[PDB]
């Protein structure tokens, strides 16, 4: 009859009370076990019988690469059984830009992996966690929802981890993607799909971390009007593997940045040019240094280069990774 | 008799030749002087009396603050003359997020000041520089554009320096303000205003740069998963007078981020928290260090802090501007 | 000390209950009365001294000019009082395009008049009503909200009754103004104002229905590829005094439409040309019949023609109200 | 060994002319021919072997279904050959909502079929036609464009026909798909794809007009506050085969509208309910009459209904096409 699904908790807002009926102020978030959540929404049972686990309880601001490593692995572990049809994961709102994209490059299965969260506290007037969680499961248990990549579900929308991001600081509808749109929507208890991702992911993925201990170090440097050359000397003097330049316009550099990058490359450090605008593609130009991010954002570019460096260190191949993913 | 407008040049995309026709990726900017641009469109003389003089002729991504001053002083002295009705400045698009906001805070006259740029080489198949210029001048020569704050014209749109920025990396409809919209639009050789900036500016700005000669130093640090903290130590060790932070949401800070921000504040450095999303408001929170930017972007916030520091240091008074400007 | 405001209810998708709590669709609108709505949110009592009046109890789509005319009268002479600082109104979203704009033209006061609603049933898992209603009272209770026009608060945003509209059939963030933005934003128990409408309204309006009891009948015709010309005949043979056209391009006409308009005009009746695209300007064009709606949508345009015809019949004058209002 | 591409001209705004270089509101359309438009863009020779063929010289305002059925076949006939690789179609802009979706249901192949237009006259400053046509032939000639469905190309974008629509009325960047997005983009002489349509089309379609001479008439009725019922009889009394209801809210009908509907559904015709909002889905509702569009606009809903009326007449059958195309 009903399918079996597992909820993996990491903290967040959906599982976090405030101190007032309408308190949307800096409070302590992520203070809820996976046991209670079952309670609050007993309507979940009509959808599918569920089992819960506790993977952690830390703010998304402090989510770390170490955890993503432990998470991806576990995920593959449970997705491999016959009594596990899908997986839902509660997570923070501040870094939901990175976490769901990392598993997109490392889970080896067709069975659904869905992230869910909330902008309003669980005690706020008109809290969204309930209904966002309710629909996050529904898509998990759906047959048609298979083989579409890692998904993100908030505000009645269904979007891919390759495109979505938090576009506004504190609004309910922050997550979106101007250019790419959504995958599908959830209306009237029914689900409607509209489009499919046209990039490589999950199964066809070449990245595997079945047995990796630590990832390389990758920094992000902003580009502005009077940017400091010395900001570069640091990461270098700390031996990081790669650097992601979040630059002006389509990743342009000043005579101070054009200089620092070279200094870095010589030392064997890989650099990638991304934009600071928030949308669009950065094209290539032999008149400038470094490699070029496709239409990946600073945040997601770091997540790519980090895994692209455990495989190889050859520019050509790397560059070709940014256009295929 | 027709109006008196002057067009101060700086050269950018609008005045930069390409190697071929369809080539709109590899080129040189600040290669074509004012004069020629004036020639390319003989229809401009139907709108006003044009006068032009070069000042920079350099790519947008390499402009420093010591040059901005020169510009503000230059435009004020031209606006005080009983025989000048408006100004029109050309600039690149890369750092067109900063420049406009600077004059909008230092120019002391209700007479019109219009910035203008292009997204393709003047040699592209359907170059926009032409129509955008005629369109900028039309606005400046209007008698109703007076007292509206610094203006930026592109793609037939009229926008406010305080809100407008480059959202996309390559498209030509890149400049927009999702939550704020535009002040006016130009359709059919006709102008239509619809809203007015509701913040402090120009004629009523408490800042006056007319007698200084060197602005303070201000850096910008990014916020992401696993972020380092030696970045902060770098700026402290070089004498920065203030730091802008690009939070992960409502400006959240990580464990290491919390740490860095304090070392700086403990040494006389003022730090303002902005946001890496793109649009939105960072709210006050006594559970974190530094000040909060209203809804200004990391880029724009840095410009407002430079000036702030040339008149004070009382953190309390600094917070108030961000809310009013 | 504590301000005091009055609440006027007229049913709507915010007063509807449903068989279950997971029923987004399929509910009876206009089930509860103002009484209940206040009892649900005990926080309101901490913002002001509330009071209500169940003027009607229906659903958005059955609203009628009769009801409108009444509603405007009852608010005028209640804002005239000294014991009333502001008034909030509850309404469906199915026609919130038309109700706010009507009052925006007929209310004679600088005091706050706020419209509010919700997209999902009061019985639903995360009904948006409670918080929407909390904010509506909040903006009415403020004093810096004076002389701004008729406001409409929904989903934490403050939009002007002249630019806002339902842009999506079922989403919970359906009200927005692509080219004009929002006036302010409610965040962290604070309201932030950014812009001001720049067209005539309220106190400076020349339309006063105080001594009127019947408005002219106006229809709306759509423009598509094989549009028939007999629809105009049918409207002409019913008395109507004016038709709003919902043209294809920027008011483009068909052969069947040219013949159409041309026919009714001679029959002494005014026709305005609007567009079906949902935003933008409709330029003059002496080579095409009828007048031109500035940037008013078919519905906003119909509201402006009824009122327009109570004070005149001159084509020329009506053609100026469309550029100023 | 570049491909062979044919250009079927229909005239449109991309072939329009005027007097002064600044004219962009009063001009004749289609005035130019396929011959001269190519003479204007030599760089095309670089991409493929081209031919031109005139089929009409009117504007999008006057496109009747007669022509469409004619065009629909000449394309199929022209694509079944081997000396034909890709074909481009020059159109106006007023009804580019319709035409593309018509062919998307009737062409039986996998070869590219792209539409292209321009919002400015050819005589205009910074005219957008040339760069547009260049990018249009560009995609057709490419081989990774097969099996992706009919494509619309303007202002550097490649969007789908089941989603694209004219958003703004006069802007140069009008064509958008708020919730769906673009399939690909064109930056620096290189194509970038990212999204795939997820619905039945071209080949898999179950529609063929190869043996059709005349199509069934379908009219659209708008939805507003005080709507007339005498509007439904006008059609019923004229032999309409179908009616699309552009309903307020999510297809919401008014008391008067409810009567006119049943009144017709009983006589014999078929009726579908869409939205006047511009986007979103209309859910199923037993409490209301008629069929429900999926998330198709009134414009597109008609074409579909009209083509489905050449096959079956069973209500339940048709409701199933709206969910699938």
Image: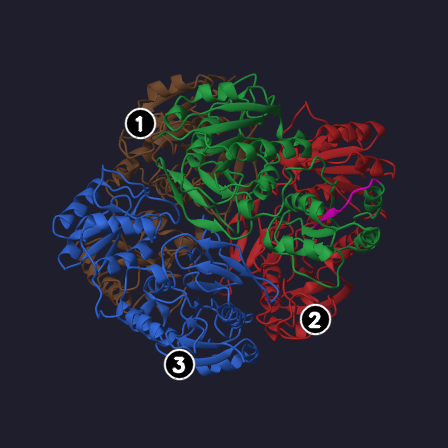
Chain colours: A brown, B blue, C green, D red
- Image coordinates of residue C119 in percent, x first then y, are 53, 31
Residue at image position (30%, 44%) is B251
Look at mark 2 in the image and give the residue it sits on. D17
Q: Secondary structure at mark 2?
A: loop
Left or right: C13 with respect to B101? right
Which of the two discs, 1 and 3, sits closer to the camera?
3
Q: Which picture quadrant has residue B33?
A: bottom left
Look at mark 3 in the image and give the residue it sits on. B53
Q: Nearer the viewer, residue D175 or C255?
A: C255
Query: Residue under mark 2: which chain is it in?
Result: D
Q: Is residue D185 above or below residue D224?
A: below
The answer to if C39 sits in the magenta stretch is no
User: What's drawn in magenta, residue-wise?
Assistant: C238-247
Q: Secondary structure at mark 3?
A: strand
Which of the two discs, 2 and 3, sits closer to the camera?
3
Look at mark 1 in the image and give the residue it sits on. A18
Q: Are marks 1 and 2 on the same chain?
A: no
Left or right: D201 with respect to A38? right
């Amino acid at each position: 009859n009903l399918p079996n699904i597992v909820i993996l908790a990491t903290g967040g807002t959906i599982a976090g009370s405030a101190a007032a009926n309408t308190q949307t102020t800096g409070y302590k978030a992520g203070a809820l076990g996976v046991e209670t959540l079952i309670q609050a929404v007993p309507e979940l049972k009509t959808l599918a019988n569920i089992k819960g686990e506790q993977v952690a309880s830390i703010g998304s601001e402090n989510m770390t690469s170490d955890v993503l490593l432990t998470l991806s692995k576990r995920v593959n572990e449970l997705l491999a059984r016959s009594d596990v049809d899908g997986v839902v994961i509660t997570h923070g709102t501040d870094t939901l830009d990175e976490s769901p994209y990392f598993l997109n490059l490392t889970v080896k299965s067709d069975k659904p992996v869905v992230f869910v969260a909330a902008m309003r506290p669980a005690t706020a007037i008109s809290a969204d966690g309930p209904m966002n969680l309710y629909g996050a499961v529904k898509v998990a248990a759906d047959k048609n929802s298979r083989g579409r990549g890692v998904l993100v579900v908030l505000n009645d929308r269904i979007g891919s981890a390759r495109f979505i991001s938090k576009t506004n600081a504190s609004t309910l509808d922050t997550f979106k993607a101007p250019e790419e749109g959504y995958l599908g929507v959830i209306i009237g208890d029914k689900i409607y799909y509209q489009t499919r991702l046209d990039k490589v992911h999950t199964t066809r993925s070449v990245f595997d971390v079945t047995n990796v201990d630590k990832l390389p170090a990758v920094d992000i440097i902003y580009g502005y009007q009077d940017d400091p050359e010395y900001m570069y000397d640091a990461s270098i003097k700390h031996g990081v593997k790669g650097i992601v330049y979040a630059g002006m316009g389509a990743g342009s550099v000043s005579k101070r940045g054009d200089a620092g990058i070279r200094k870095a490359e010589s030392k064997g450090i890989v650099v990638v040019r991304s934009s600071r605008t928030g949308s669009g593609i950065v094209p290539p130009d032999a008149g400038q240094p470094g490699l070029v991010a496709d239409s990946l954002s600073p945040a997601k570019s770091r997540i790519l280069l980090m895994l692209a460096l455990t495989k190889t260190t050859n520019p050509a191949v790397i560059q070709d990774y940014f256009h295929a993913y």
